[PDB]
Amino acid sequence: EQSNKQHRKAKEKNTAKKKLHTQGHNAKAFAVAAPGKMARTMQRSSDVN
Amino acid sequence: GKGKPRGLNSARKLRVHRRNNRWAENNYKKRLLGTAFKSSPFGGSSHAKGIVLEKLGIESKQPNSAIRKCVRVQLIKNGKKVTAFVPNDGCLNFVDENDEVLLAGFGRKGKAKGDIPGVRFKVVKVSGVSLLALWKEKKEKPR
RNA sequence: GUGAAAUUCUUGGAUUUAUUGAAGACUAACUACUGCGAAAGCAUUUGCCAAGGACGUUUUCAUUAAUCAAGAACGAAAGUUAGGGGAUCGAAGAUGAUCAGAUACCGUCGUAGUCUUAACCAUAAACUAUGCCGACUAGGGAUCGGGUGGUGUUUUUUUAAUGACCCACUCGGCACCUUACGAGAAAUCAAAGUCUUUGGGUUCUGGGGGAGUAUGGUCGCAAGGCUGAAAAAGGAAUUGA
RNA sequence: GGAUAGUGGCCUACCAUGGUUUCAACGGGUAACGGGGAAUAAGGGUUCGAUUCCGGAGAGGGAGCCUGAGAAACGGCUACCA
Image 1 (cartoon, rainbow over the protein chains, first blue to last red):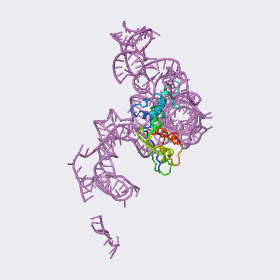
Image 2 (tube, helix red, strand yellow):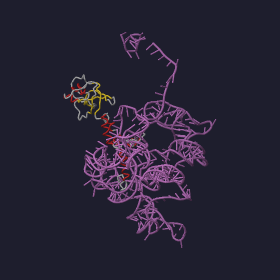
Image 3 (spheres, helix red, strand yellow):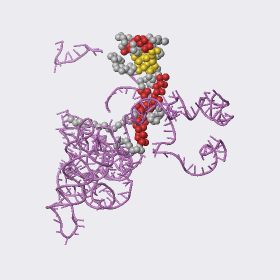
Image 4 (spheres, helix red, strand yellow):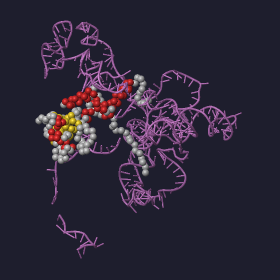
């Protein structure tokens, strides 16, 4: 009997970079300037709602 | 030489390269975009608010089984039905119908003998007062 | 011609034999763990045109260098457009035999292609499954190119060559055999090493498998618009009653 | 030249055709007032700083002016939107 090892070819889509750019706008650009403050204010505001 | 530059003037490259790869991270991207709380159990909040639809297991026989402790409430900021624990079938009595319960996470640490899995919420306040308060007879449920 | 056959061609003599002729490819044995090239690739002879590595050098300039996006050059086979030629093999196709067994699934003919010029295409298990430049860190032979030396055979001697072999040394190659005081999960690796946790220069890149699901994350692709039927031993049987 | 407390494309004439940019200009985002400071990690860094002091800007939103040494003031005025 023969054992013919197979080989992988190439990647299709496993990249955080292209995943960011895959929507029309630049999700990287449309961001904030104070992530921690966003986090705590969204916490507080969701609770009040 | 480890792949990155090293010369004493290459700070522009070290900085810019770090910025792009820092984006390639995952906790970082979510933190800057504002989506960790779209992953969270029920939105931003720490407690949610719901309406008791119906008490399941009213007709079960052995008292204080999980299917007795369970109810079914619809979260009001979605109109979305989810089931939820309540300790103490007595407290099952304290919560009846159209009650505006305040739900919290369950956060169980270890399973029990017959615990229903897939039931992640617990009732904390009912019609505005605390279940433990009612149960301990400190307060009284105001209709 | 196959495992077996069969279409087919053959008294106007086929297959075979002898002597020739033409046509287009192709370059056997010699062919090697040998050579050349940036890779793809490249084997008949002689000539011309330039080009190249290595080696030799008590020649010359004197930092002119390394890594590098864009772009460019070239890029097997197949393929496309337009011409040319068209022996051979030959996707599609047309056909024969469909005989058990496929253990022994093919035969005859053949468009396009194969070949060539001028343009496109730019992909391969294009592989040494591993970015480049520099330096150091183990022994051993062989082999190809160049040079130096030694020694005798092969050679020859006032004409035109003065090359072959053997030996030591030597730069530079294609690879090989032993091992690593090293590395690694292991196979293995002369780099995939460079004394416990880390800085010789530089570019690009990163944050398994099947399944089960949600899709507003999105792109494609559909139809018809006169048209219809009503239970059985009332068996089996050269084997039965 | 006009204007101003005064410099200056500040504005107006008339001239040249320049200025910034892979050493990232221009544009977009900002749950961006800036700093002293606060938290914390062994260092390196990271995150917070509306908030007792310093600076800036604002008084529902555009614009405009009067007094006065000092205001484009709003517990002053005028009109416009709400």
